[PDB]
DNA sequence: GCTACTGGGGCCGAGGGTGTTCCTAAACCGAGCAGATATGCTC
DNA sequence: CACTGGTGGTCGCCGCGGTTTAGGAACACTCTAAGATATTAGA
DNA sequence: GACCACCAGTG
DNA sequence: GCCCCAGTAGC
């Protein structure tokens, strides 16, 4: 049971309702909750199955060095990058 | 996508809804009030949803709540349970057939009754007593326990019918979560051993085993304070009691421990 | 002793279940008139209606069109424990189990089951005759049959006839499960099928499965329409409405269980 | 040490850079991190002193019933509501 | 609003940056690529930022890093330390006066050296030995520890060469230099942040980072070097990234950042 | 100890030399051994090669404000040479050398030697009295209203114009002084009159020249009463430091103040 | 609502007697019946 | 990129052999020289 | 009668 | 030369 945040963008309303089934949507396309690893894998299954055009980013609490991890689906100007193991986000130009 | 349920220990205890129509929007369980305020509800992340008078649930909402394993419970006056809707085939055949097997055999039924008696009260049940005799003993001790807590919290008590309001609200919440757990594990709520006949007999047994631990005395406290809004304080205290005691996580091992007396 | 409601609000007027549709036609329903209310899509029930149904014991069941699916039901798990313990008594005793299975065989096919056969032997005869019936339907309706092939993951990557058969069987499990719930029995307690939460549904549905339900799947298979699953679902809906199969399944259930020679409840 | 999420809306770039000092901006106005109680309350002081016109919501992991808690600054169409202790979000009409 | 550093224990150990100009945008530490790709660096949440060849830091960037107490370390080949921008006047008077007090007295100096020996090898140092003698004993122990770890992990081992002009299929020495360089980085950051002087050493002396070498060498072979040997046996395509990743994991598990300062206080506790 | 100030340009390496390319293209070629300390003013960007060269020849880099008004960062953090830090530390820990250094600070600040039979706290008292009289004298001379020195550190705007000017002046002075202490290679935390705080030595040396030019200029700006007084005081201290060469002159003053201990210098 | 772009202005948010003390998949197994260089279908 | 308005189309996203096993702030202090000769403005 | 897909129009 | 801010388009 760790903390979860799912940020959606350009996502069709099916995935938005489906995410609202389990997670609290505190801002447009920003969902937050507290789920286990299995439930998180199921929610990511929903994300991969229902977005189809938009981009989604999912982050959850862990025991890594930064204390959390995140994962992306689809393309966004903000793209994750690897720095010798540590994952950050970089903003691509136009 | 499948949209399968979440384990019961992972979700929130209970949510109360009032005076609004309940719709499904883009797949979500939404509550709309008379003014137009849409309010999404994490239907999949709550054990049971309580519907108060004034709610108007739609078909897709009942289907949706059913698919995510979230028991709907219509309650009326003082939160007393009126009706309920859940999964139509959400009974596990091995658990259901084991329970019914224990219920058919008179010997195993006596074993289960004695187990419930020995779990509700610290002392073992009196030996060589029939089912009805143990039922009467447990009933007399229930009356003496209600009167005992009544003297401890200093509220006038003429019998189990303000104090009946608080007791009915808290015990009604416990019956809600207990019914949700019973349906979730696959057992039947109508097949009871101590209580019989009523369609929620097993819920009355399992929940009555543990209601006097923390649920009833808190309702006596709220009954003595007697605030202007008793139901809300009772609900709050019920959620804190369910979270602290982790009742939802230890309801199923209580059922399996009771039915384990059948060897 | 039951009624389907759709496309309207279910409210209470003078102690009666009133159904107010879109055109304003109110359907007043006295309490003693129906034992179950089958709620179809497009229905919104009020709190007073659920309160009335509770205080008179009416069974509410949220279903699809004509009971094609069973989405939810009031008194979940079973309201009457006597009927549940009755069915369980019939299923735990091996002798009564074989009696009920034999009655299922004699009601599914005209001839009684071969004498002194166990449950697994009758299951083998049942499966073999089901194979021959698949072949017979294939030749009669003139469709190429390769077997009961279906991948549980990719529905689209499957044979069209197996899609039609699958949709037809799903609708049949719908009406059947609705009938078992209306009668007041547990869908999981089965005699031929056992273990899964809808075993009884599989048995009772299997009694009549190849009577115009699966043959309708082969019929829709001949035409090869654009969306065979929808055509099969709607065809099954129409057959359930005309043939009144839901209403006629309850006596079948009561007799199948009645073959146990044990006093049924009332 | 618990997980932290900050969603900003219509805040001046000062607050966005200040949040970029400690947290990872995974989407426009969406920051994620893992901080202590002191660092969290400091970050909130930054939000209060630096937003001045927009709305911010901060959700951090806890050991409550929902597993997390959140607070808000400013006004948003999505407003928290109290349901018998459980805090949800309502979407107000125009 | 003021901007203050967060405790070192709550931080990521290290970040390596290369081939881009480091600017400050809206008060943020930003790494801009030659292609225009901006990459924000959570400078306040890192203990060291290693700057590889290709980086062009701005005045505002160096100021900002020093303000949130994040050490800047310009780094050469195999991660070796070249330079370091840090917090000016960031040393505590009581701490620095205690350290210098211990270094000025010869007896207290030998006390601190013996404490470093006992903490490094577990067993107390031989009695009636000077600083040069404990330095030679320490040298032999280090040599035999390198050889022993080499035979354990099964790595070709000859010399422990520091000069990179000796590595022309010699990856083990590169891994040792990179790992120990990461440790030297976080240890220097811990010493500066704690308020001590990295130049005032006891075992190592005259070097500009003698105290860093002492404290880091106390806990070097506990976790950091064996990991370098593990990376060395599994011949990698990019040894630097593997060694950095492994050192990061080691720092998280062994809780090195949180245990550095109390180790320093335990070392300097030799003289009352 | 030579030094050079650089602003508004890119610092790169050409042919093993520090080249500085400014906004207009003026390349400043700087031989590698021509300067011991580079003061990086606002607007400068350092390439990795430059830091590598300065590192390999031991050049101290300091990121400062204009003319040393603030000290933001510095290379060789904490101190690169242990001999100087232990020299200053030995002077501070021994009370006799401490009182010698303090007496040199007194004699250099005013001109007259302090009285012989005096302790450290007594010299602190004489200093306090004389700076009180100096506050009153400067206030009466420039004709600004004086009601004391105190202020509110929790809010800068809740204070006198004169206290704001004085505080800004002493701030810039602490900048240039700290820059000097770092360029000489000594510890800004090891003080003799001031003790305990991480910039005690900066306060010590700063007190020597505090009331010669910067505080008089603070009373001048306070008398003129501009719109933004802190910016005017800071720019005025910037111009004073540039024209009077305050940074360069501060270092030999440090070397003398420490040399008063009659103990062999590091060299 | 976020992002980009372009002039215009500034190089900037401090102050310092000191030191103590306290606040869930797979493997395994039943049947019939067609039809057979046997397994294959079906339950 | 999110929210919303109207219209036309659906009533849905299925398949069922059964069972066992794999750290600040508060206070408490120096000292001086003027001068309310006590107390105070400065370090 | 309840719900969804679609196709834009605006800030 | 580096960086913030104000205003104004643009989607």
Image (cartoon, coloured by chain):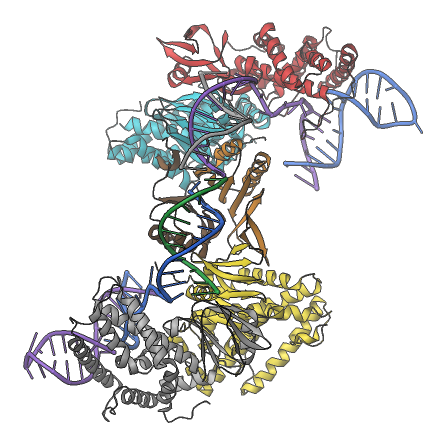
Chain colours: A orange, B cyan, C red, D brown, E yellow, G blue, H purple, J green
Q: Position of residue C108 (x, y in %)?
A: 69, 10
> In this orientation, does residue E101 appear?
yes
Q: Quadrant of the N terminus of chain B?
A: top right
Q: Position of residue B186 (x, y in %)?
A: 54, 27
Q: Quadrant of the C terminus of chain B?
A: top right
Residue B69 shows in the view: no
Q: Nearer the viewer, residue A26 or E94?
A: A26
* Relative side of B27 to C144, left or right: left
Does B191 sit left or right of D53 as displayed? right
Residue nearest the viewer, comparing E237 with E179? E237
Name the quadrant containing residue B222: top left
* Left or right: where B165 falls relative to C167: left
Q: Quadrant of residue C22?
A: top left
Q: Position of residue G31 (x, y in %)?
A: 77, 20
Q: How many marks?
A: 0
Q: Residue at x 54, y 52 (%)?
A: A90
Q: Is residue G30 above or below residue E214?
A: above
Image quarter of residue B242: top left
> Which one is in front, C132 or H14?
H14
Q: Is residue C156 above or below residue E85?
A: above
Instruction: Residue C49: give x, y in percent of width and height.
Output: 40, 15
Residue at image position (74%, 18%) is: C127
């Amino acid at each position: 049971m760790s903390m979860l945040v799912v940020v959606t963008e350009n996502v069709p309303p099916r995935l938005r309702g489906r995410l609202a089934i389990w997670l609290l949507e505190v801002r447009a396309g920003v969902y937050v909750g507290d789920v286990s690893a299995k439930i998180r894998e199921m929610i990511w299954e929903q994300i991969a199955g229902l977005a189809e055009e938009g981009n989604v980013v999912m982050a959850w609490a862990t025991n890594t060095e930064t204390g959390f991890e995140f994962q992306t689906f689809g393309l966004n100007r903000r793209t994750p990058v690897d720095l010798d193991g540590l994952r950050l986000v970089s903003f691509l130009p136009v | 996508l499948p949209l399968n349920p979440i384990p019961l220990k992972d979700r929130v205890s209970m949510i109360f809804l009032q005076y609004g129509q309940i719709d499904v929007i883009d797949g979500a369980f939404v509550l709309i009030d008379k003014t137009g305020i849409r309010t999404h509800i994490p239907v999949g992340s709550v054990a049971c949803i309580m519907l108060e008078p004034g709610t108007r649930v739609s078909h897709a909402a009942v289907r949706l709540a059913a698919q995510v394993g979230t028991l709907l419970v219509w309650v009326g006056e003082a939160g007393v349970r009126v009706y309920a809707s859940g999964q139509p085939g959400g009974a596990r055949s091995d658990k259901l057939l084991y329970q019914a097997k224990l219920a058919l055999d008179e010997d195993l039924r006596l074993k289960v009754v004695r187990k419930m008696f020995e779990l509700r009260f610290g002392e073992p049940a009196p030996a060589r007593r029939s089912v009805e005799q143990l039922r009467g003993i447990e009933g007399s001790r229930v009356r003496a326990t209600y009167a005992l807590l009544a003297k401890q919290y200093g509220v006038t008590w003429n019998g189990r019918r303000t104090i009946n309001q608080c007791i009915s609200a808290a015990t009604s919440c416990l019956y809600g979560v207990t019914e949700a757990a019973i349906l979730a594990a696959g057992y039947a709520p109508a097949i009871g051993f101590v209580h019989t006949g009523k369609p929620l007999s097993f819920v009355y047994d399992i929940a009555d085993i543990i209601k006097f631990d923390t649920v009833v005395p808190k309702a006596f406290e709220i009954a003595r304070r007697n605030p202007g809004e008793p139901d809300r304080e009772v609900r709050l205290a019920c959620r804190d009691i369910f979270r602290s005691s982790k009742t939802l996580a230890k309801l199923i091992p209580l059922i399996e421990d009771v039915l384990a007396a059948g060897e």
